[PDB]
Length: 94
Image 1 (tube, one colour):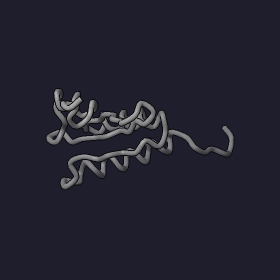
Image 2 (cartoon, helix red, strand yellow):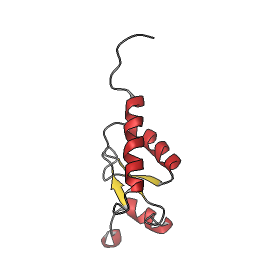
Image 3 (spheres, helix red, strand yellow):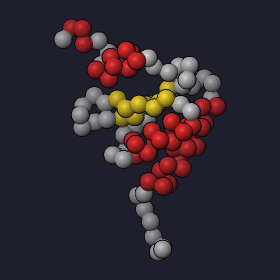
């Protein structure tokens, strides 16, 4: 128990709780695209979501770059769609 704390998860979590909820109440907003600020922040947010009552997921273009996204219950993504979403828009070409 000392005085002095920075760059932690706790604070981050709280912020997520407020954001998530705000998005839930907001009808106009059907989804939200979060930015990969930290490496763990991803898992943290995911938890806060599943608890809030929304759909959470992670999608990134490059293995190194991985962002987190969230969708609503009704506007939630589908199984097949989810797989394709991660793989990309339409790899049909190759």
